[PDB]
Amino acid sequence: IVGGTASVRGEWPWQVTLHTTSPTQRHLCGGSIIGNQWILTAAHCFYGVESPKILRVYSGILNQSEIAEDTSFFGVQEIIIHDQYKMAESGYDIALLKLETTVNYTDSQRPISLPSKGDRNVIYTDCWVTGWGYRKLRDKIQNTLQKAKIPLVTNEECQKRYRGHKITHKMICAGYREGGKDACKGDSGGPLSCKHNEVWHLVGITSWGEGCAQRERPGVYTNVVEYVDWILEKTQA
């Protein structure tokens, strides 16, 4: 996250840090708890990942330093990637993680509500992006979870900033015309959380962007509301 600050512990109880143990354990991507054994994240996060066995999901984490060999984690039973996904910039950058065991909800770990199709019209003015990602273009994974408040921009406006791309309605963007605040490498798969009427909804999933926090280069996120049907179909046993 660029231009953000340290989060308060428990401030984003739905945020998880997805690690890979190959070759050695490290943070791989962000993610969101949406159900007792379901994590919503980005599809591009699993490039080169052949098996769910090298994955580990940590919940209730503020600092990566908290994660050690003796820290409990959730194993991943199955990686479900949208069948139309090819790459981040083409859309469909969404994936589900079915955990081997269920998450016991508590103040430090609980689910975020999916957006409602009835809310496509509501306007969010209180949206935040979080993660342990880069704070600069050539940086490293950060220890303390970062947060940054960022305004949503219309798709018409976003498209004007990405003339070489096709910004579809299944994508949503957020950023400051002047830049300064944005998600970045390492934050991928993490949530774009917007609070409306005292309730938080998972509006987007950090997906891509030209560089990070650059002027007139809005961050691009998966428009979650467009996938609520896909999510229901994929999580329904």
Image (spheres, helix red, strand yellow):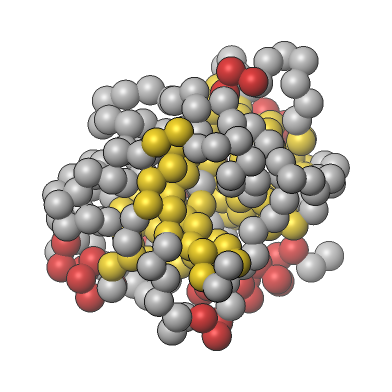
- Picture coordinates of residue 133 (x, y %)? 42, 33
Q: Quadrant of residue 96?
A: bottom right
Whether residue 115 can be seen here: yes
**Above/below status of 86 relative to 142:** below
Q: How many marks?
A: 0
- Picture coordinates of residue 144 (x, y %)? 50, 27
**Above/below status of 75 relative to 120:** above
Query: Which quadrant is the N terminus positioned in?
Result: top left
Left or right: where does residue 7 sit relative to residue 55?
Answer: left
Which residue sits at x=45%, y=33%? 6
- Picture coordinates of residue 135 (x, y %)? 32, 31
Of residues 10 and 32, the one drawn nearer to the viewer in this rendering: 10
Left or right: where does residue 90 sit relative to residue 225?
Answer: left
Q: Quadrant of residue 89?
A: bottom left
Q: Quadrant of residue 152?
A: bottom left
Which residue sits at x=55%, y=37%? 8
Left or right: where does residue 216 sit relative to residue 92?
Answer: left
Which residue sits at x=15%, y=68%? 160
Query: Which quadrant is the C terminus positioned in?
Result: bottom right
**Above/below status of 160 relative to 182:** below
Whether residue 45 can be seen here: no
- Picture coordinates of residue 161 (x, y %)? 16, 61
